Amino acid sequence: MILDVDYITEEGKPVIRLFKKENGKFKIEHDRTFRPYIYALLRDDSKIEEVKKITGERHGKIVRIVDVEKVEKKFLGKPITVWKLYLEHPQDQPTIREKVREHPAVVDIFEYDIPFAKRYLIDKGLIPMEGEEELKILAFAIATLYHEGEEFGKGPIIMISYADENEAKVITWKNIDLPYVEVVSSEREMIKRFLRIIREKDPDIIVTYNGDSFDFPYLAKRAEKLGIKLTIGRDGSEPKMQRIGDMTAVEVKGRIHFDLYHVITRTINLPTYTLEAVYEAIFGKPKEKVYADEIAKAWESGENLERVAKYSMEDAKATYELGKEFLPMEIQLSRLIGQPLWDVSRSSTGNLVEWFLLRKAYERNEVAPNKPSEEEYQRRLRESYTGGFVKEPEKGLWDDIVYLDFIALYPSIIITHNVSPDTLNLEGCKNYDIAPQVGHKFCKDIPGFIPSLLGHLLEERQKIKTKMKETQDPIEKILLDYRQKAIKLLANSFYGYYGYAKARWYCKECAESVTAWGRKYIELVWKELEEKFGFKVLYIDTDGLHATIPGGESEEIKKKALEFVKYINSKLPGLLELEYEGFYKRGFFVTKKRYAVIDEEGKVITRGLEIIAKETQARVLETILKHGDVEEAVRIVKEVIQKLANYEIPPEKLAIYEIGPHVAVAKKLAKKHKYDAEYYIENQVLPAVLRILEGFGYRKEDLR
């Protein structure tokens, strides 16, 4: 399988290198056949003779066009002729662009700024991470001695921990009595040990959490001071710092450095992205945290190093376990987009769509649009985008609530109404659909570029999903599930990509229309559900609705909802489709994006209603949702505020674990005095509880 691809310069010529793994053996395949190029669109094709001899410059040398070739291409569907100007080196493209474009006969040039290594994979039709191979994965993390606001690297590396399928160990240079700790002469030898472990294990993928920014640079500066080369690459090379956007990543030749931090960021949203939080959110079970001050005290003492060696071992053990869960997802992406995992895992979802479309463009013989200019880029970043329909909810405490929503709404709209730049207001178009309120017309004679790709993606997902019912092989079933996750993520990225400033296939009109159509069909369901079925819609947001039959029986509401989805789907066009998603026993709605519901199992879901103060507002939700008693909830608030004045509540519950609030905290460096009360009522209890009770017409006066 193809793991990575770069290129090196030999005697002025570009040489591609395909880093591979085949039959459990590593090999590098060189390729000197490929040639970089750019496209030229001319007024007059006879003027090509003048364009052929246009000269450029680089490092004082003379850069010229080595070959030219006439080719038929498509541009936004419409046929077009272009000249393929070949060059010696990829780095000749900027200078040849500058001067070829200045020619009066040349109208524009295209596909001039695609990196050479990625150009090779697209053109050769090479997809990385294909086939079945036993890839060896290894994770690692490091513990450092921090002291003072000091330079990055002055503190010695206290521990280097690592973990794989078989084991999880710690390498250090102090006497510790643990069975997974390995003691060594000094820091220098600790680093040399780590190099031996990487050498013996010889991993295909090295996994870190935040390795680009912290672990590799800190190891490198340390290794520089100690006079020791980091022979981590499979050709003995050191880790190389490389840039992409506003990020400096770390590269390892022969292997794939997989930094987990970048994959978790664009996927799920959390308050903070610590290694402990991410582990708990994913796996459920908790992970203890040891802090810098605890490490600094225990290290210089010589005792209490068992606690730090535990934390360091678990850092490596957790990173491996997270890596094992997110890597199979990411290899399917890289296999779906068709670029290497090093790049794909550090790419934003908008840029992953770009690399997908550039590959597909080549399969369809179609010329890509250029990146926007700096003036065009800043223009797009200024414009605003109108969101989905949100309704001001019906207030009060409601019973037996059904939630209905659309399946893949925006993708289904893009396919049904053929929404893309190449079909926008097409000249000489026979049959077209008009977007509501915005009036943009999309041609439906031929399926466009993006709508056709997306339609195929959703087809392939259904095949995988159907085959998953059938399969009994657990390895296949889990493989299919990731393939299905990868396609889904990629498919939901297309909407956002249309409004993405940097995108080549940018189309605000397409994005306006997708949102506009979404608002039409949500309101259609709203009208059809309240008139023909007699329901009362409680709240609507973007692609889903909460509703019920006020005072109606629980079992009847479910039945009439399951009937409505069958009905409404007969009216909805193409891929548009509604589904029965869930049922709730009770629920109330304060305002937009602010509500709380409760399922039949008693589990209480919330949104917008967030942070003794956290305990009370949780106790308020329970008495409202479980028992349906708003008056009882008010008594609880009156009881809690009374305990604050009389101090009947115990200590510690009033404490907060974290120039500002830390004025008295800075002094601590080296039964009584329980006076705080007004603070806990005004700043903590009321703001949390009022957020809920405002919907039922209560004020600060009622509580206080």
Image (cartoon, helix red, strand yellow):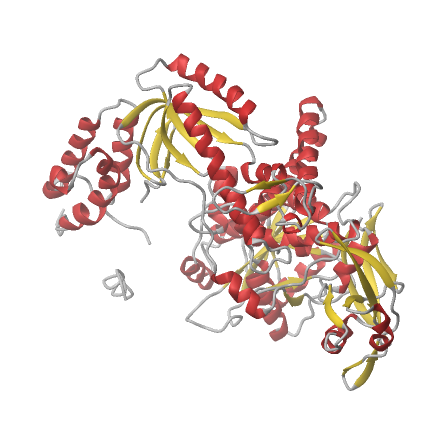
Q: Specify the quadrant that holds the C terminus.
A: top left
Say whether residue 496 is left or right of residue 605: right
Q: Does the image show residue 612?
A: no
Q: Residue at x 42, y 29 (%)?
A: 526
Q: Residue at x 37, y 32 (%)?
A: 539
Say whether residue 218 is left or right of residue 114: left
Q: Residue at x 68, y 39 (%)?
A: 457
- Quadrant hosting residue 297: bottom left
Say whether residue 162 is left or right of residue 99: left
Q: Position of residue 563 (x, y in %)?
A: 49, 17
Indicate whether 193 appears above or below 162. below
Q: Position of residue 361 (x, y in %)?
A: 74, 52
Q: Position of residue 494 (x, y in %)?
A: 60, 47
Q: Position of residue 670 (x, y in %)?
A: 28, 66
Query: Which residue is farthest bottom?
Result: 60
From the viewer's side, name the closer residue of 494 and 4.
Answer: 494
